[PDB]
Amino acid sequence: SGQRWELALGRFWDYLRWVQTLSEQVQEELLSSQVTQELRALMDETMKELKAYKSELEEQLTPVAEETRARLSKELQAAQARLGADMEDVCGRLVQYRGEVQAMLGQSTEELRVRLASHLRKLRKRLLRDADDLQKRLAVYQAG
């Protein structure tokens, strides 16, 4: 619904979609730490806005039993953690690539790139899946 945190995640997502192409410029920036640096910044902004959003949502809540409210807040916090961990996993996989290329000592990295692409697809599937769940939980959080 165009929340600030969603637009932030959208920018992280668009950038990652670009990285997935493994185009010439992506390949260049992947050997430097430019891609992981720009990706962590986008991840940080997303989590930052996410936290601020949750805090603001809690100003207009429907009153329920301390227990079910306490549970929904624990459930919401877990979904948040998952998202951050997903983004961290992506960054980590990209760091592994940088090192595997270096270890090749100049050899063709075409096979390494085929495998990186395959893996990134699965990691991105996981991230999208977790983002959707988090977004659904946030939508029904206030009603309790």
Image: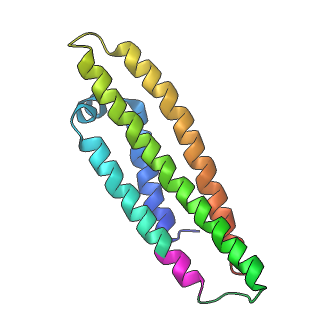
Which residue is rendered at x = 29% and y = 29% of the image?
Answer: 98
Which residue is rendered at x = 54% and y = 58% of the image?
Answer: 81
Which residue is rendered at x = 24% and y = 21% of the image?
Answer: 102
In this picture, is 13 found above or below 124?
Answer: below
Question: Where is residue 123 shown, x and y percent of the image?
Answer: 53, 38
Residue bounds of the magenta highlight: 52-58
Q: Can residue 29 be seen in this view?
A: yes
Q: Magenta span has 19?
A: no
In this picture, is 144 found above or below 109?
Answer: below
- Depth check: 135 or 65 in front? 65
Q: In which quadrant is the N terminus drawn?
A: bottom right
Q: Magenta span has 56?
A: yes
- Lateral position of residue 74 relative to residue 110, left or right: right
- Lateral position of residue 33 relative to residue 85, left or right: left
In this picture, is 110 found above or below 70?
Answer: above
Question: Where is residue 22 shown, x and y percent of the image?
Answer: 37, 29
Q: Residue 59: name its quadrant.
A: bottom right
Q: Can residue 144 be seen in this view?
A: no
Which residue is rendered at x = 44% and y = 41% of the image?
Answer: 90
- Lateral position of residue 40 relative to residue 141, left or right: left
Residue that lies at the very extreme toward the front in this rendered image:
67
In this picture, is 8 found above or below 34?
Answer: below
**Which SS type dominates the magenta stretch?**
helix
